[PDB]
RNA sequence: UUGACCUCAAAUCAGGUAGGAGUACCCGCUGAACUUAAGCAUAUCAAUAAGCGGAGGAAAAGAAACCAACCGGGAUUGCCUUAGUAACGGCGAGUGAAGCGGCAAAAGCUCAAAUUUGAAAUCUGGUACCUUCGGUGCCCGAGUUGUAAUUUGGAGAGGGCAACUUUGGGGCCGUUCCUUGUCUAUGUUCCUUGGAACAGGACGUCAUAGAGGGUGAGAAUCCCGUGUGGCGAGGAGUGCGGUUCUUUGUAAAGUGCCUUCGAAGAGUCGAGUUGUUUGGGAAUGCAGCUCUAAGUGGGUGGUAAAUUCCAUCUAAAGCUAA
RNA sequence: CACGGACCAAGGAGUCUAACGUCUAUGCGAGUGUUUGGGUGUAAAACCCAUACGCGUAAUGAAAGUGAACGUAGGUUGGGGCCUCGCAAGAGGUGCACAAUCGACCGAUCCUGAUGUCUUCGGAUGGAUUUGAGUAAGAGCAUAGCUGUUGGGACCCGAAAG
RNA sequence: AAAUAUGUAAGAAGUCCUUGUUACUUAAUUGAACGUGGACAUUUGAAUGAAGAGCUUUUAGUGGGCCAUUUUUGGUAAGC
RNA sequence: GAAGACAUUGUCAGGUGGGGAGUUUGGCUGGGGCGGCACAUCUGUUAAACGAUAACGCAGAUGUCCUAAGGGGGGCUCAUG
């Protein structure tokens, strides 16, 4: 769509967009990543501080599969509660009639928190959970059952 | 080089890739031949499904340890748990895992159930001339779907005794991390003179 | 072994109905055999001891199984294969130069 | 001395094979520099250009000395994804994947290692004949330094017990396969200009047939075709559909029970140096020099090595349709 | 009195991708992405679906790993809108988004050290001018295009070379 | 110590009165960082003015410079 | 016949090695080679009453030194005539 391109909008104006008292010279400052630890170090300091160098210990055969941490929280949580009977376990919320939750057979192993929920007793079969997270689960009726 | 503040990208384009770059102009082209492959196969194959039985079995890793998917074969302990052997299982149309086996009972169940299913589904005929034909289904996997065979029941009652789950694995953290270190203090307290 | 059911700990994972694994002929690849051990013994009396074998048998009767031992890692490699080697050597010292 | 064995051979020797082309694409190797870094040796370029060797329609790849560390997964491939991340690097420029997930696609298996030991039971060549991609009457040699048969890691043999089960394969013509041979609706009626009718305007017809072209200008309707199936041809062929000839058969094989056994591939494995390649970093593969192992033992377990098991395949031998 | 340009006709110079940053447009909307593949098709169109995985919501640490409510998600000022009263003006209250700001929430770090302790695990509370690409009742996913991108022939032409 | 150039200052985020918090601090709820409510509308506090005041976004091109004024360095002097 | 487990030959380490490769071989700068550093710096000035402010401008310093010449207090007053 060369139609709405400012090319036809500068055609004949000599310089064609890059000047004539300096212009565009193929690779002016360099090619790819111009002298980072050299003259282009003023572009990294303030805009990209920290690129060059090493950090902490190195990890070998570090698959993100053995480092899988599907974290969730309190503000929502009722997201994994199926709509159909979600309303049933909300207002008419009771014990013995507790909601069974398999978060691993869902894809959210870690269960943490944020903005509370309505006081309801629900079973949550998780993998890992936070300290202050399980704190709020108990005060309402919620429970935890660790599986894998 | 660099022009003001832009995003830092590591692009792989400084070779003969402009010789070995295949834009799929044969995309759905092969998709069509895929049907004709199965279609031509069945033209001489008369009433065969063009696909055998793929077992069921949960995936490994800490990520796929919750989704039981379709496996490969059925081992000699399950072809024997079938009523014959693995040489009779494949000459009919059932998979056989020569290198894999039976590890968890839970799966052996949902599979031997699925074993008698396809075993009552295999409309096999003799080899003389009579051999009676009887329709045919062009499927086997999508025919007996695996929608996570047994996960749990929706309704249950609250069981509160006092575990926290957090402090259970916080000390189970120490259990797993101070196994051999508190075992070196166990041999230390195993030889006092 | 059956896990602990929970996430991590002594046994990380769920403890579901475990089964006892059927026969794996594989793990017993290195089997003694009365056909390989009968014919392996005739090897110790038809070829007997090798130059570096004779060199290391007395090498023991020299400074001990620390001199011929650290010399076997150079005349071989793996420290475990190196001491599996010093094993059949004291076996030839008694079962040959004695009765 | 006679028939000989053991070894090198041997002539336009019988009957046969191997040598080039081609290098879009596979496998090897080889082996860059420019450029990049604003110079440049590091590295990049590039495990790439040229050079060189041997095939195919696919090829290498592929049945585990795999992967993981899971309730574990279960030949490798291709693909999205992983992830331009882990990882390498004056840790400067830059370089950079694999398990499994989704998927298409799906295949299995076979040789040495054993006593045939009541009988070389396995075959070349060649020759009268014959129903021939061959064979029988017959004979040598190959060959007992191991051929048949035997079994092989998923296993499996000898002894017995006491039972059951699976069919083997050609003619005949169709279907399945490749090219196909060929018929195949519709009009040439008229007016207006026109060299000429395929034209401005009509007037009919076909429309499972307005693809397209051609024909003396815009042709759906004139020529071929088209769309649509039919009737024949040359062969392929027992996949399928079965019928006729052959019961071939005191033929072999798979599955169940107890015991004993259970052979499983080496100047290889790994280790120690050089250096090449590198995601692979106190070895990722690889070649060389040297060393030179074992049998509940050994390869792997991505920070070196010592140390008890665990997990995990059975290397070093082979083909294999997508 | 620098340079090309005798003169005329047609080729001929900020192009595309791979992945992105800017501004905005639109579907859905904490979802989204159908199109890798599988069903269908007058047939390369279109149409349909999946399990996926991506990104996002979750961050803070070198990693172990830990992982966001004193409080109506809040104290203080200015604020659009609404509201009510008012002749107007405004008095006054309710003050989204947002701007300045005090404590607080979580990680890492520096501290302290109640509990019990397979006797060194474990670590509430009160804390520190510390601290971070966050929370303070999601805004992204997916697409087209516009200015800039950097890997490539990379605005078009040319070096000695190698 | 001139002229000439220069920074700040001219209000509802202000001033006058009350007095509530603090682990601050003070001999001292003393003071102070900070609020509650009470009094005053544009003579609400010199002049004058505004394609509106304010503010984030975002990317090109330029990063060889040269003349005049007075002050002025070098330099004989310079169209240096 | 000679030479003989030393040479030959396979492989490392060691040495030599512009004979061969590849490359740089600072720049600023009254052109530049040369000197200098007007290069990271800094004393007063140049700077024309804030500040900011060229030049190979000008009269110069910088790479170290001190467990006391430093820290803190106490007593004392120095050059000099």
Image: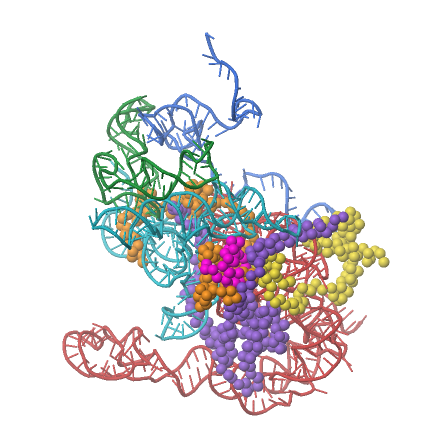
Chain colours: A orange, B purple, C yellow, D red, E cyan, F green, G blue
Q: Which residue occupies 59% across, 62% down?
A: C5
Q: Is residue B41 visible?
A: no
Q: Which residue occupies 50% across, 45% down?
A: A53
- The quarter of the picture where residue A3 lies is bottom left
- Is residue B121 within the magenta segment? no
In the image, is E79 to the left or to the right of C55?
A: left
Residue extending farthest to the right is: C99
**What is the number of callouts on the image?**
0
Magenta stretch: give its range: A117-143
Q: Which residue occupies 30% across, 54% down?
A: A5
Q: Is residue D132 above or below residue A38?
A: below
Q: Is residue B89 above or below residue F73?
A: below
Residues A146 and B37: in front is A146
Percent x, y of residue C85: 73, 55
Percent x, y of residue B71: 55, 68
Q: Is residue D159 above or below residue F61?
A: below
Q: Is residue E6 above or below residue B48?
A: above
Percent x, y of residue A81: 47, 64
Percent x, y of residue B112: 58, 74
Q: Is residue B39 visible?
A: yes
């Amino acid at each position: 769509p060369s139609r709405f391109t400012k090319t036809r909008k500068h055609r004949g104006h000599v310089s064609a967009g890059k000047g004539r008292i300096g212009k565009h010279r193929k690779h002016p400052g360099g090619r790819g990543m111009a002298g980072g630890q050299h003259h282009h170090r003023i572009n990294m300091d303030k805009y990209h501080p920290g690129y060059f160098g090493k950090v902490g210990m190195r990890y070998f055969h570090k698959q993100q599969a053995h480092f899988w941490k599907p974290v969730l929280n309190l503000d929502k949580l009722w997201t994994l509660i199926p709509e159909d009977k979600r309303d049933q376990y909300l207002k008419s919320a009771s014990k013995e009639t507790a909601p069974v939750i398999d978060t691993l057979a869902a894809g959210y192993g870690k269960i943490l928190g944020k903005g509370r929920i309505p006081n309801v007793p629900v079973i949550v079969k998780a993998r890992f959970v936070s300290k202050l997270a399980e704190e709020k689960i108990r005060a309402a009726g919620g429970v935890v059952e660790l599986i894998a | 080089a660099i022009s003001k503040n832009l995003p830092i990208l590591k692009n792989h384009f400084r070779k003969h890739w402009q010789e070995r770059v295949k834009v799929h102009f044969d995309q759905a082209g092969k998709k069509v031949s895929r049907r004709n492959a199965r279609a031509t196969r069945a033209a001489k194959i008369a009433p065969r499904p063009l696909d055998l039985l793929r077992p069921v079995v949960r995936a490994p890793t800490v990520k796929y340890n919750r989704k039981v998917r379709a496996g490969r074969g059925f081992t000699l302990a399950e072809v024997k748990a079938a009523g014959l052997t693995a040489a009779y299982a494949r000459t009919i149309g059932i998979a056989v895992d020569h290198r894999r086996q039976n590890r968890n009972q839970e799966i052996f169940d949902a599979n031997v159930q699925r074993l008698k299913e396809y075993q009552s589904k295999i409309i096999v005929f003799p080899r003389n001339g009579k051999a009676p034909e009887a329709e045919q289904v062009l499927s086997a996997a999508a025919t007996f779907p695996i929608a996570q065979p047994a996960t749990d029941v929706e309704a249950r009652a609250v069981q509160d005794n006092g575990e926290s789950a957090f402090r259970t694995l916080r000390l189970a953290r120490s259990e797993k991390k101070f196994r051999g270190i508190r075992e070196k203090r166990a041999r230390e307290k195993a030889e006092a003179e | 072994t059956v896990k602990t059911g929970i996430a991590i700990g002594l046994n990380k994972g769920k403890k579901v109905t475990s089964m006892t694994p059927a026969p794996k002929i594989s793990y017993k690849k290195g089997a003694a055999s009365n056909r390989t051990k009968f014919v392996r013994s005739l090897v110790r009396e038809i070829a007997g001891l090798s130059p570096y074998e004779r060199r290391l048998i007395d090498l023991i009767r020299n400074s001990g199984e620390k001199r011929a031992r650290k010399v076997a890692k150079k005349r071989l490699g793996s420290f475990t294969r190196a001491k599996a080697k010093v094993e059949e050597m004291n076996n030839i010292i008694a079962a040959s130069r004695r009765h």
